[PDB]
Amino acid sequence: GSMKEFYLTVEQIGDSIFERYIDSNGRERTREVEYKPSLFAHCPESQATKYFDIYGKPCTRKLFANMRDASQWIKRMEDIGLEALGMDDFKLAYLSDTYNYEIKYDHTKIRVANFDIEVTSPDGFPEPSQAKHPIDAITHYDSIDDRFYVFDLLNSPYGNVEEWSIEIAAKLQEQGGDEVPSEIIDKIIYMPFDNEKELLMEYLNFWQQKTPVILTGWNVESFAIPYVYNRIKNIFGESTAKRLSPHRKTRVKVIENMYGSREIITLFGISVLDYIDLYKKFSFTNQPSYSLDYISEFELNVGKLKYDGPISKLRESNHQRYISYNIIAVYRVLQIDAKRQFINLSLDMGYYAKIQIQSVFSPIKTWDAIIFNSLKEQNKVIPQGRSHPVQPYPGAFVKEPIPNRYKYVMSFDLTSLYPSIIRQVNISPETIAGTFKVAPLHDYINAVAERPSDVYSCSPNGMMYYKDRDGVVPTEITKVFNQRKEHKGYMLAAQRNGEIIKEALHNPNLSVDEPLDVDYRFDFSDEIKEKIKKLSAKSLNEMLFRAQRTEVAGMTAQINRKLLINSLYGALGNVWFRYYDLRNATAITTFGQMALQWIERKVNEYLNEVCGTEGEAFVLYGDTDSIYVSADKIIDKVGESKFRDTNHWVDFLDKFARERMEPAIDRGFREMCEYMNNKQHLMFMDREAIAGPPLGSKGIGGFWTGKKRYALNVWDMEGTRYAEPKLKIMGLETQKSSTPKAVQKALKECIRRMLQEGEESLQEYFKEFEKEFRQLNYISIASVSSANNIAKYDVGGFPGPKCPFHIRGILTYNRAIKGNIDAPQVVEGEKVYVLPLREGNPFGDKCIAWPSGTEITDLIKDDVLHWMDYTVLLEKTFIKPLEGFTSAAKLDYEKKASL
Amino acid sequence: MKEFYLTVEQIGDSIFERYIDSNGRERTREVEYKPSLFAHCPESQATKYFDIYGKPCTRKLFANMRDASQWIKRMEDIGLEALGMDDFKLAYLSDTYNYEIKYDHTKIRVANFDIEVTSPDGFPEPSQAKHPIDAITHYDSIDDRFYVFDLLNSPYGNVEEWSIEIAAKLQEQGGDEVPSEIIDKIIYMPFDNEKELLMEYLNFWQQKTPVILTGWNVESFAIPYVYNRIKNIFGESTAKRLSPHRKTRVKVIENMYGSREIITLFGISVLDYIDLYKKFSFTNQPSYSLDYISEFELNVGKLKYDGPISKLRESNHQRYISYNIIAVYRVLQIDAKRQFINLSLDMGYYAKIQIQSVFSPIKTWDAIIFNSLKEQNKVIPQGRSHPVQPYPGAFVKEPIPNRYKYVMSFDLTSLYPSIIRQVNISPETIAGTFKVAPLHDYINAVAERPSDVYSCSPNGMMYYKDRDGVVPTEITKVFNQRKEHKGYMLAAQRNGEIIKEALHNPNLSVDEPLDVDYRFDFSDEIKEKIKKLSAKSLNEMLFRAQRTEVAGMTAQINRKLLINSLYGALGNVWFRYYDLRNATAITTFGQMALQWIERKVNEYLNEVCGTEGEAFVLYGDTDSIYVSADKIIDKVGESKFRDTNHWVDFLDKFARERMEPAIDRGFREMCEYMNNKQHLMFMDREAIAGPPLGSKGIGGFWTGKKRYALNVWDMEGTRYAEPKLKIMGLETQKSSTPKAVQKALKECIRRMLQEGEESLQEYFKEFEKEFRQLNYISIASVSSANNIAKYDVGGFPGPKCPFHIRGILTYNRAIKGNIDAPQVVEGEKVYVLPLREGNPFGDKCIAWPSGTEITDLIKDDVLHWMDYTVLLEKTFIKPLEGFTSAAKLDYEKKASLFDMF
DNA sequence: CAAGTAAGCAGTCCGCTC
DNA sequence: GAGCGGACTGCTTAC
DNA sequence: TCAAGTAAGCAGTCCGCTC
DNA sequence: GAGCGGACTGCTTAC
Ligand SMILES: O=c1ccn([C@H]2C[C@H](O)[C@@H](COP(=O)(O)NP(=O)(O)OP(=O)(O)O)O2)c(=O)[nH]1
Ligand SMILES: Nc1nc2c(ncn2[C@@H]2O[C@H](COP(=O)(O)O)[C@@H](O)[C@H]2O)c(=O)[nH]1
Ligand SMILES: Nc1nc2c(ncn2[C@@H]2O[C@H](COP(=O)(O)O)[C@@H](O)[C@H]2O)c(=O)[nH]1
Ligand SMILES: [Ca+2]
Ligand SMILES: [Ca+2]
Ligand SMILES: [Mg+2]
């Protein structure tokens, strides 16, 4: 045929590679291949051939008859103390050999399955490890069929019920409907069942015919998959359960972390990407709850499906709603992926690197595969992975700021610093050239230490690198970095475009039209800008949605390519990385420290010079690769009173940054490259934030409380001129998932008023929030914490020594729900709401905690509401942080007592 | 006399010390000890103080100890080394006791107590102490009395008083059989209520406050249970009266699998005898129950009783209390034998540490070295951080599995301490590095000479010869002190046979014991004056003779443990003097030395026997070579010998006169090659092994590394009346192997080595026939039980569940809902039995706590559904197949008609 | 489960000042 | 006795 | 298993492979 | 289904 072939899944099972793939005729195929791998040994110079290790030292290829021999050869070589070289993960070698080209994949041919089960349980949480309760609903969406297959148990030990009606389902809540979105109604294939055996046999047969390649859902890896597997195992036997693998192989793998161990089913020939796990790695959020209800609301702004009574009883109560719920749960994940596009990101990284798609969770595995593939094309031979001891190594510099208001601020930030350092210095395992005598870092920062080398590219940690060779790490990181730049470009264009539409919405023309057909990844032409100011509110609001969805797509693509390249840096400091080397890891961080503090000096020198001052500190702060510059003296040299409005002084500072500061900064960094004799100048420092108060207001513009704790009123970020000023808040309690939701909102308004409006406005809102606090929903004002090691501090159900406050809260909960089976149980390693309790409370302790994202069981709710300590809660979560902000910013959130 | 500390603690800025004063009276003092640490100087300010690298240091006296510790952090942040003893109570001890401490154990209050706690609802967790203490027995070393506290009334029993006369009687005369030697040492005290009992004991504790506190599980059970039980009634401050500094604290003991809690009683030294036993016994026991260790050590039986322990006090309060008393006595009997308390006192006072710190070689050795360096106005380096990582260890030759008829073994003397001294290894004696040939090239002496200037190890490390290392120096002094104190012990032995040959017909007179030193051979003056003494005054002179002997032994055992301890510390990141390159210099030097002298011995024997490239060295491990003597015996004829002693004499003569000089020459060449500071690779002949002359015995066999058996006639010049089996590694040696299978396999080996294949085949039949009639405990396997919970999946085995843990889960299901049923303890050991298919327990094995009978609830069913066939095959036949395969014989003449069925 | 370090605040324990 | 600060754990950010 | 070290054996589980 | 051996965990030696 005329289609390029690409793998779907791959496994090693003994001496066979089992591959699912799409063939030249674009059909799904499977094949068992007795892969003949090759490894490599350091040979003498005379025996030379086309194969050299990364240091250029020659190797002979050793072809093996099968894979189990190769692995044995490695163990034997490890006894002799001789290095066994090459790709020891044979299915990477196979993927590499079979697909010796850039893979173009067609996602319309990749079966992506999306499923959720319901298990009615009278006696608490149905543990998937023993699946002792009937499965009474499955919904399974298939991306090739674009259908929702619904499987519905009518008869179970916990009730006989009637068929679900798609007719009822479609309707609105009011006329007994379930509000199943109408755009999936014609995509639902319903199948009822008299017994569970029939339901399960039907789903397995169905699974044989529509075998997922990508399997996803919410908590599918930890609940649904193990629960279905063991439910089928317990009824029919193990052999029948293993039909969930198209190669009939499963492992009951033990996943370990620092607080215990859990069980997961590996289905060989399937790629499980649990969406909860994609969300945690790729979303760059930290959420107080990871329930689908909660993530659905945050991402889609779509509310919970309400239901009366406990989940354990919904089926008897309203099976019609039970089944609709199951169906929408599946849809929710598809909605979330449409927005975030984590499946597309996964496929993209998994095919770029030639790895199993689930290996996108592991940057070590992704990069091992990329660097392997890269070295193999040059007939070069990767090192044996070695054992190394974990030990600390130093990281970034963070300047101690003077706690203060800062009125006018411009920030600058190095482009992809650590990847840029890797490229600039030529930092690679095989580019190490030697070392030099290390002066103190201060001496390099101030340029009074002797030039390290006239021959080699240097870091100030004393490492020297060849300028005449290209390192594999520089080469391969450059490629991913360029992708990241391309996608960031699209993101910022989408961002700029959004503000134009936002601006056009202020004066919406009352007309009837349609959205304009544009690509949001590129700055609107003057022409399109003209046609936008003649649109209706309806048409503009649809275009704003399309822009923001384009920005989110850019954000996912760019920030996760940045994670991958930053994770190659990190991989250098991870003992399990093939190319682990603390000299190279600390070459990067130590260079970074010099670069930041070097450019701090250079910017101070330059601004003293423009402002006719001496030894003034203009750089008030920086962290890792950022500087924050006080612009007060720049504004004052013009005279604040000559500016027409805010956008006038913003324009001026924008021009000053670009035309005066950027050239000075590049001069500074070119001199630093020369001092270190680096391969390429790549220390590029873009203007980010222009921040200050609205002109003529008593806003303070910004404050720092200390390291990693500040707020700026931002008018322009990285060339995006905002319709309305945006708060950039880093580190403060507004940004922390542990801070109660209502208090996040309260503190942010406190900050907005401080920066924008000033002390009197702040003092006005403080009084306001104090008044409405005790009438706020109890969940909205509860603290959140992760609960680790509940058992370490559980001493016959009471706090042991050094018991953390949130753990105390959980022990208090556990005591109060003892011998109530249907009470919701706190899960080790998950998150809890926390409330303090007034002295004299019935729970016998000073706080209580319950599972985050839930109402507290009705058994105890009323007593909790009655004994909530509102005074301590307000003091701890609101007033204490606010006192931190206001002491920093040198104003008051209240006037003290006056008779 | 001279003043010695009892206990010491840092509480903030106050050292609290209990001590004996010059009058011999127990005292306390709080002290605001002003510590001193040290910093690096430029030459200008140099004074008497130098760090171990020589470089000069300023003393920095602090007002309190907390600013010294803060200064440390200040200095750390700065990246400046802060020299000297960070453990301030050691510096104090050093300052306060600047002389060899002479201690008097009759002035040290050693208490050991045991409590009983009647409980219906299973094990009474000490962390909650939710049941009445209904018995305590508390022996005091100074009073020589057992104080019995006996609760007469409780929620579980209103019972009568305990009769010391019914106690004394024999178990036939309705008695408890309480030893007669203690009956007149018991101070009984019944109580009508527990608060009364508890208050008195707390007040009795207040007079007679333990310095050394011991017992069996006192640390993990008895102490916390007494503490918390008193807290929970009388409140915290009252419970803190168990510290004589009213300062107590709850400690978090963390291991690889979870954590427990103990009560640190500040101002008491707790040496739980279970923990002393584990550390100092160098056994591995299938159980560490008092009852099991008592049986093993003393041969004293099992304190017996009917029904559960929860219903003993009610059923037979009279036996209950006797049990409680005899429990405490058992531990005294055990310490009478092993003397671990006295050894502990000796080492602590030697090192000038808390006595409880003898548990730690790192602490003990840090203190010893600090005190010596202080004396030379030198300054210990700061504790530094090092990444936990492996380093290479001993060499072990791969043996050819075979019978080996005639074997002679040679062992290097204290190898690792000797390499440290030989190569002068210390952090401050590191001088540089060299190009490293493969180890084989150093073994074969074809590698080029590392250095002409520095003492070398072949891991590439080079050391100054022109100075003595801190570590070498210190080890040499403890070596020298061992010799010192064994001399003293033997001189006091020889002096004690004099006095006991002057007691023959003692001059009936009125004299007084001579004021003599017993650590030296009596001058002929004293020998004369000793005969003209009375019986009284001789017998006192012999009591002092023998206490000089016991003290000499205690001290030299002490020194030996320290010598063998030190290498361990050197390999541990938390050791001040830890260096990785130093660790692997020690061990790689050891590898060379063994394989060097293997080459040398092979070369010499080939020359002596007129052969070439014959392998004489069949095996070696770390510090040992085993030499095949067959060809040596064949020079003279096997037939030419009169008896076994003749050829043993012959090999003893040949080793000492021929092989040892050849070995000394070998090791001398090696010393020059590595340019070492002194030659200390000394290799004594150890075993001579073979069959009885004219027998069909095979003499010995190897199955592999760390698995062999020798019939030994002579060890280090001691000629045995009867041959002794030296068995290493084999299942006879392993605590996991059933007691009865240990004995059977040993008799199998004995017959193989001494008698031959047919004798083996005769015994095999006999043990097979008797196996099914043996007691179930005697044929049960033993295993430690770690991570039970990990593999427990709703009461059933999880993935990769180990066999013994499957056994524990079977037991748990079987005793579920029986609260009075004995529970398996996480980290403790279990008996394991396989079960025949279709058994009611629902699995293929069961496990229960070791050193116990399995609970009567299930005992009958286990006995019925025991799989004897699987048991015999796994524990006995499979290992025997290993031995006989290696030795190239068979435990059966042929396969049975049944096996060919 | 899945690359890295720097560093903030909440809370416990405990000894010190007040 | 109350309040504080240092040494610590636990959690959660910023980069 | 609070409290020195590494080398290396066997029992048993999982699993592929061969009979 | 049983047996073997390799890759692993668990345990217990030797020194
Ligand atoms: O998760 C992270 C974030 C940052 N870092 C390090 C390396 C990286 O270069 C730097 C991040 O600084 P920024 O957050 O400003 N991002 P970066 O400079 O990489 O890229 P850019 O500024 O172009 O977005 O800190 C990590 O190692 N891991
Ligand atoms: N060049 C190279 N080939 C490797 C390495 N590890 C495994 N191989 C395998 O060795 C073979 C190389 O043969 P070639 O591609 O030159 O015909 C392929 O099967 C490839 O997967 C490695 O590190 N370098
Ligand atoms: N010599 C020495 N004394 C130390 C060291 N660490 C702490 N010290 C203490 O410093 C003081 C020195 O007093 P000196 O021995 O000079 O009379 C003593 O109290 C001693 O305990 C050390 O490393 N060397
Ligand atoms: Ca940056
Ligand atoms: Ca047959
Ligand atoms: Mg027989």
Image: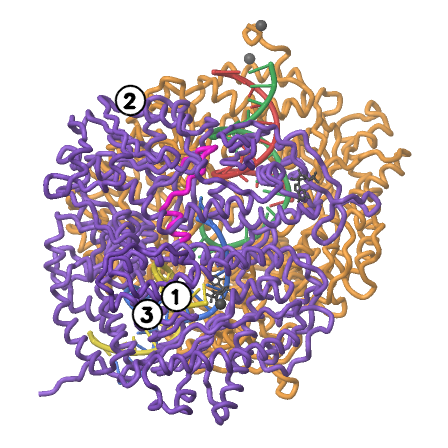
Chain colours: A purple, B orange, C blue, D yellow, E green, F red
Q: Position of residue B398 (x, y in %)?
A: 70, 36
* Cα–Cα gap, marks 3 and 1: 27 Å
Q: Which numbered dot is residue A686?
A: none
Q: Residue at x 75, y 30 (%)?
A: B406
Circles 2 and 3 on the same subunit: yes
Please name the amino acid that badge 3 sits on: Leu
Q: Chain of mark 3?
A: A
Q: Position of residue B46 (x, y in %)?
A: 63, 85
Quarter holding ligand 6:
top right
- Dot 2 corresponds to which residue? A197
Whether A274 is among the magenta residues is yes
Q: Chain of mark 1?
A: A
Q: Secondary structure at mark 3?
A: loop
B775 on left or right of A838: right
Q: Any atom of ligand 5 within 8 Å of the CB at mark 2?
A: no
Q: Residue at x 34, y 23 (%)?
A: B842
Q: Secondary structure at mark 2?
A: helix
Q: Quadrant of residue A224?
A: top left
Point out the tag, 2 or 3, that comes first from the N-terminus.
2
Residue B524 visible here: no
Q: Nearer the viewer, mark 3 or mark 1?
A: 1
* Cα–Cα gap, marks 1 and 2: 57 Å
Q: Nearer the viewer, residue B528 or B688?
A: B688
Q: Position of residue B713 (x, y in %)?
A: 70, 33
Point out the tag, 1 or 2, that comes first from the N-terminus.
2
Q: Nearer the viewer, residue B556 or B477?
A: B477
Q: Chain of mark 2?
A: A
User: The N terminus of chain A appears in which quarter of the rendering?
Assistant: top right
Please name the amino acid that badge 1 sits on: Arg
Q: Nearer the viewer, residue B521 or A592?
A: A592
